[PDB]
Amino acid sequence: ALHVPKAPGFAQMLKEGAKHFSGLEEAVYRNIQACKELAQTTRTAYGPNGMNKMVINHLEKLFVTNDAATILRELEVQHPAAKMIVMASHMQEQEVGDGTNFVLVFAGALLELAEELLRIGLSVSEVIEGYEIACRKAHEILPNLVCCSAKNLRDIDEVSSLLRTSIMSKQYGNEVFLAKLIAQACVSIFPDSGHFNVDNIRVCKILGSGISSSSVLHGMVFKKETEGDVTSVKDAKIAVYSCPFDGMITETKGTVLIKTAEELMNFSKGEENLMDAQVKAIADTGANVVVTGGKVADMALHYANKYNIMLVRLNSKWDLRRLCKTVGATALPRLTPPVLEEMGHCDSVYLSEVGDTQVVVFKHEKEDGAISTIVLRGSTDNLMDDIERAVDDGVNTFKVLTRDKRLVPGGGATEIELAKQITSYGETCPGLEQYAIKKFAEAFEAIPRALAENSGVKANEVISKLYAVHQEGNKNVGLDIEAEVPAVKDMLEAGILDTYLGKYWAIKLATNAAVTVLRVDQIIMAKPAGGPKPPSGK
Amino acid sequence: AAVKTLNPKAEVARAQAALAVNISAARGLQDVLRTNLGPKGTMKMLVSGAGDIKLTKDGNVLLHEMQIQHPTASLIAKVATAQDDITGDGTTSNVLIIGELLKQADLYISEGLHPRIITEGFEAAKEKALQFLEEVKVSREMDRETLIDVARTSLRTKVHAELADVLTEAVVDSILAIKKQDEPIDLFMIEIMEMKHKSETDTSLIRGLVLDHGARHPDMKKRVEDAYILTCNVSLEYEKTEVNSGFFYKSAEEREKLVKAERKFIEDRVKKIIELKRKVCGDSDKGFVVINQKGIDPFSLDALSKEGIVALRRAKRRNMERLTLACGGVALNSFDDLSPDCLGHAGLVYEYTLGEEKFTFIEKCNNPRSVTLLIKGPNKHTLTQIKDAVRDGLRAVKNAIDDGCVVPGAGAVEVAMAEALIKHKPSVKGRAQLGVQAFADALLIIPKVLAQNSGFDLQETLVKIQAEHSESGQLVGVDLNTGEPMVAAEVGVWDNYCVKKQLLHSCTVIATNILLVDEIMRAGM
Amino acid sequence: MAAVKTLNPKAEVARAQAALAVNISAARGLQDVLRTNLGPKGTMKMLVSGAGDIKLTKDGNVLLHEMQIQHPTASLIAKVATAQDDITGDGTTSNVLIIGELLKQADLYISEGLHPRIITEGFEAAKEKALQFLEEVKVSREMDRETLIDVARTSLRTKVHAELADVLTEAVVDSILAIKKQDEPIDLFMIEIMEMKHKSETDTSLIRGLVLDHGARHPDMKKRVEDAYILTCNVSLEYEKTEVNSGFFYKSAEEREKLVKAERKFIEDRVKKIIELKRKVCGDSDKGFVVINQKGIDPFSLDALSKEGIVALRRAKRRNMERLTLACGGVALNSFDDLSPDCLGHAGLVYEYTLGEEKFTFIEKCNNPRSVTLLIKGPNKHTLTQIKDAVRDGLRAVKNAIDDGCVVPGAGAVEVAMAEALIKHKPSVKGRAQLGVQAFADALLIIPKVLAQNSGFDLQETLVKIQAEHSESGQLVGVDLNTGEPMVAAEVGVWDNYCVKKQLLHSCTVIATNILLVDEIMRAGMS
Amino acid sequence: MQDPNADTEWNDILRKKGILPPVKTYEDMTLEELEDHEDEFNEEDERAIEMYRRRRLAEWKATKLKNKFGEVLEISGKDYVQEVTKAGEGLWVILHLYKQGIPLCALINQHLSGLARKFPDVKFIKAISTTCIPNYPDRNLPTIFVYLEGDIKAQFIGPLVFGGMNLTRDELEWKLSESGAIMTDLEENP
Ligand SMILES: Nc1ncnc2c1ncn2[C@@H]1O[C@H](COP(=O)(O)OP(=O)(O)O)[C@@H](O)[C@H]1O
Ligand SMILES: Nc1ncnc2c1ncn2[C@@H]1O[C@H](COP(=O)(O)OP(=O)(O)O)[C@@H](O)[C@H]1O
Ligand SMILES: Nc1ncnc2c1ncn2[C@@H]1O[C@H](COP(=O)(O)OP(=O)(O)O)[C@@H](O)[C@H]1O
Ligand SMILES: [Mg+2]
Ligand SMILES: [Mg+2]
Ligand SMILES: [Mg+2]
């Protein structure tokens, strides 16, 4: 009588290293606890006062950031429910580009409050009913909280003021400079058509001169050198080839079949004469710059130097495509001279040395083009990666504004108003759903609570002040970061605004994630694999 | 024992012990799967050894994902896999009825009764139950409303209620489109494409096709309005000769001539396509879309783009038929004698980029005999769950159409068949009547577990329901919101006659074969 | 994996359904092992220790403690059976069977979502009604030799072979009917049980006297004494050294010799007292004199007593003091200070029996011995152990039939009748505890079922026949193990102990109730 | 290995292929202990308890026979050969070579006087080193020789190795039991 045996049935038939959790205690509460640990792991990075984290991944690579999605990717989250919340956060990053930390905070809060409600005696089904109905009310409410709209995305001062909020949470100290840069870049792009592509904003990270040395470039920069003797061109007539800069060869197999001393004597001279003819036809179309996606031959380079053509070699195909979009050219699969339409043009193409790095710059003078580059200077690669993430946030905000121009107040104002209105809705709903509705409402309080906690003030004082001021009627009031004591101010008049779409999708995804985590009742983990990882994800 | 004297490393379970093993394993499976049954069931999460997550309520998926190494469990998993392969639904109920037959047989075998007599009673009860099933089956003209109720009964068990109300219309409309009068429904003609960007309630039915790839030439259009679709299976890339030809030249000029010539073979097929395009749309009003099951090299892509053709390459071997049935052309393996009659029409063709991948929509076809279900969702596991649910629902509607009969649900047929078996028992000669009783108490596991899952007392609910069915005769089942009896045919709770028949047959057969097992033996070393 | 495993990681835990499954599975396993022990048509199990020792047994308690089991539920049930055996001597197999069957019949309804609390309420109600029916059907009988013979037969025929049971019956009944004093509880300690390993097992006899497992250690002492005065003493007759560390000091070999002669004067004096009593009570060599000392006797004292014709046995058992003073009729002494012929008992025969390397001393032809011995003769150690177990069962059976002057019909008759009464009582129970009552009834019904199973008959057919006969007639009927037909247990002489049946009902109900209410088995005292 | 060996199936497959190697009884109770209970023992046990009690009584009487002297005595050098080299066969002898002058010697002699009564089986003798050994060095005392059958079994020599002036009647007892002479029941505490 000194060992409890496994019970007959599933407990015995289960494999060796497999685990089975069932019920509120073994499954639901453990999942909620894991998600709570996750939310706690990422809470201290929320907001402008959010602190950076130094995550080292399994490859000993270092990420210094307060970007929630980046931290989550580089963490090795192993609990499945936390994995699900992270999946939701990554869907937020994909759909909107900003708001991943909101998704985490809100999901963790909803799950904590759901645990509370299950302890007081509600069923997961009723909790889910209340959470879903309250999410529907939140979506019904949010459109009415919209205060501002963009009204112009071709301007640079309005666009800078609009991107400032998204690029403030990240890179708080310097947010006017970066917002100016990202506005310049975004408005050079964004044509007369309503479509805006974020991949057309390129970021080149060069090292050594502080972030204030960053710049925008209407064109392209390649950390390459020139293949030939020419390094500068002032009226670029670029010709782009996806083929190498060499004589075309057979796809099957080629053999030089010599049968006479004359053929042997003439073969090499014929090859060079052919190359000379090819490159001279290219030069005679007026092209002064040739950009090949493949290799360069020594003879072809010789003759390009002879005819004063700048040769550039882009190993990547995406780089070639983006250069074609930049210059207005067409990648030719043959070494045939380009027609007047297949040619691209640039007000300048030159080789420069930005810092230690040598670069080839295709620079337009016009304040437009199909692609724009942000040259980020900085004393550290990690610092520049963080600033690139801030740039990505600003650009994704610009795209969200191209999609939906509506704006809600930030700094917790929207969250407090949502909490208030959903509490007022739950107070009217009778039945067991009111508890869950009121908890869904109170969950919004987690956002200004995190902002206050990170600013370095008492979250309770802040939340009480916000509730009091929002009772008086002010829906645009949120907390003040610029105050050693708990304080509040008009988010609108201050210009601290978020995107209607950002909040919409964050609430939707966080609610779906929490509700999904709750619907789990049994977990049957398998023994961990030594498999060479998922085959499709490579 | 006998085997262990010859093969010392042999494992053996004899007579009663063997029975003990098998029934125990069955009951173990039942304990796991009992919660899967019905819309009030709970979703289980299953984590692979790699860490992949599955959220499922499906009996077959749950079986194959549980971590089990039992021979009886293997037998029952295979029976469920056959149930799923042929009918698409009925796996959880299959496992439950198997487990309950074994339990109810243990009830009498523990009393020293021989399993042979229980199996005779099983056979008698199977016959009478199949008869009562064919009698109570509802032969109904399969209208959109009936099919909607059927698909609801399946999707509400497999997914959330709002998402089930969406997938219902999606699935019923999908089948009612690919359906030809008195000609078995080929579910292959319903492509199933999943996109991972939007909410799960955005899952839709595209009355056309969605290819998981697009054009690889950038200068190719991203949207085509009035499109001629050329479905081909012809290589448009460089093909080397079978006989290892090899090129021999004496001069750079000859090398250039051979390089220009070696592509003439494929340039000619591209020229054929381009001439067809010019002859069928002499202006830029219409569009022209080539969809090739084989490759297209960059040179051909350039040649076709220059003429304004949108070329997608390496499509799926099934998309050939799906496109010829949706658009309405002819799929070609050669351009020898191609005519405008070989072309299909699509009132819209466009491209959608999602992260790093591209999709191509072909919509506004005239009367497509092939459609697609676009499974949208925010998570891989949401997409997998919706795929499983739509598989179940498609099979359900297909079976209700094929078998023009339909059976009431909510355990109603099970209750009524139990009563009929209990009234039939005296007509059985010998102690096989006890096996009949066991069969009845086995049939009664469906309503019981439904009550168990809705949060009600099994015994009270079952007596209420049987009382209501004896006083009225109305085929009644469980109301999962009140625990009271309800007329399933009146409230729209429908099950598939094929599924119930397959349950009876397969469950009886496997349970009989297990009960007659008297020795489990591993002696192969 | 749970609450306890978060604090003590090396903790084993079975919760609610798992705990119930564990316990019921173990109970069903014990029942499956012990089902064959029940009844005379049962089979004997052989049990081989880790040393290689052999036990042939049909006894539930012996089988339990000898099976190789490590289950907590099995430990609980083993202790319940051990209490049953310590207090009643019989009822252990039936105890285990009824426990297992109560657990099974309760699982029948708990698998159907019924709460175990309601089953335990039904168990308590059924216990009340069953105890009432038991007191009602009990047969209060004047315990005559024939009734006691039938009782002891019903027990010994279950424990041993039929011829050996027909012998042990007379032996056991005569033994108890001899050591018994009118209206005075029976001290079974007054029945010594000595086993001899030389002859056939049917030579097992009742010596109306005593058999000591030792004899005289002086060869010149007689090996047979006819008319014997027995002196039962607890006085050391060997050399005892002083408590206070005395030691001898002498200056000459003659003084050493004087001290050697003197150091024994103390024990020589007690030997002389014995010898003087012997001479005063039997002045000739006609009668005999037997000293039986609970303490030692040195060779000098043995010589001194042999010279006078006394047979002295030494280092007898502390119980033999009372057994000899009650059989022979003397007084056991711790000193020979003032001893008189009234301190002596009489034995019409005393003799010695050598068996291999050991000696036995028989004291027979006592007048009216209130103490006797059962001589267990048999050819094998395991035969002797088996007969010891059987005679324990039979002695307890007759003692209980006398103490509780009532006696209950056997062959599952009382169980059948109690099941019918419980089933007729069911409607008077309020709520779903009626199912607990049904479970109690079908659990009680395992005794006739197993009896049929072991006699080689169909449980269901025999049980329906028996219940039909009991409902149409009302005669308390049970299983006829040779025909499978119903038979009147009181008419055919198949008797059980009312005390045993009551102890079964009480203890089985209690342990089954407590097991069903277990919702967590937990081993967390590690580290 | 390439990966960390943990609860995973990959390591298990590698292992299967051959890579990644993987009061007890009356038997012991003394005369005093046997009296302590007496009643506890069951009579069936008491039958063999009689034999074990006779065995223990015989052993105790044997030890009584063996305890010849039980007290410290002094031998001169002249008779040393008879008292030590030719002591009783198998009799453990402990000789304390000492001068009365050295106080540590007197402490050791007091401890030996106690141990002699504590251990009446072992022979305890003391002797002046100058009178046992011709010109025994002054700074080489106390000397504890342990003898058996005339053979030296141990020799604790020196005013420092013996264990310091803090030497109670316990650590010396252990040092003497080191060679297995007095056979105490403890461990070296200090
Ligand atoms: N100047 C500011 N004052 C107060 N709150 C701000 C300010 N700038 C940004 N925020 C708030 O910070 C939150 C977003 O910060 P961030 O850490 O980027 O989270 P997320 O990744 O969810 O956008 C929003 O609630 C936003 O309103
Ligand atoms: N709304 C409902 N009310 C009551 N019973 C239902 C309802 N919907 C389905 N059922 C019943 O629940 C049972 C199990 O459903 P499902 O899990 O889809 O079958 P399976 O167990 O084969 O997967 C079916 O027998 C069905 O008749
Ligand atoms: N000759 C017999 N015929 C029928 N039943 C009998 C006979 N002898 C004994 N029995 C019954 O068999 C049962 C089991 O006997 P036994 O094994 O001695 O009891 P236990 O199970 O307590 O060891 C008793 O209830 C007794 O009444
Ligand atoms: Mg942000
Ligand atoms: Mg289904
Ligand atoms: Mg008995």
Image: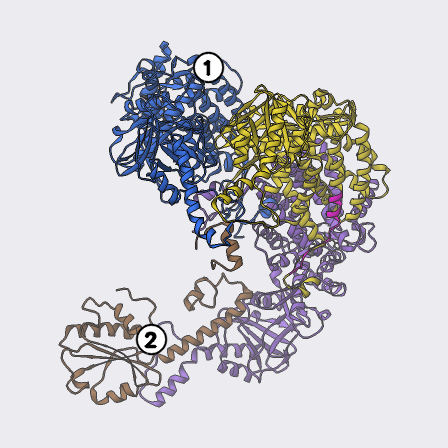
Chain colours: A blue, B yellow, C purple, D brown
Tell me which amino acid carries mark 2. Answer: Gly
- In the structure shown, which secondary structural element does the residue marked by tag 2 occupy? loop
Secondary structure beneath label 1: helix
- Give the number of callouts: 2
Find residue D79 and report its image quarter: bottom left
Q: Residues within 10 Å of mark 1 (few under 14, many from 20)?
A: some
Q: Chain of mark 2?
A: D
The residue positioned 34% from the left and 81% from the top of the image is C248
Q: Is residue A370 above or below residue C116?
A: above
Mark carried by residue D180: 2
Residue D128 appears left or right of A466: left
- Residue closest to the eye, C449 or C500: C449
Q: Residues within 10 Å of mark 2 (few under 14, many from 20)?
A: some
The x, y position of residue B387, in whole percent, is: 60, 32
- Residue at figure coordinates x 43%, y 42% from the top left: A274
- Residues shaded magenta: B509-525
Which residue appears at 43% of the width and 43% of the height? C7
Of the residues tagged 2 and 1, which is closer to the observer?
1
Q: CA distance from mark 2 to mark 1?
A: 94 Å
Q: Residue C244: x, y in percent?
A: 35, 72
Q: Which residue is mark 1?
A: A141
Above/below status of A300 relative to C263: above
User: Which residue occupies the extreme top position in the image?
Assistant: A473
The kind of residue tagged 1 is: Ile
Answer yes or no: is residue B206 visible.
no
Question: In front here: C336 or D62?
Answer: D62
Q: Nearer the viewer, residue A221 or A455?
A: A221
Residue C158 colored magenta? no
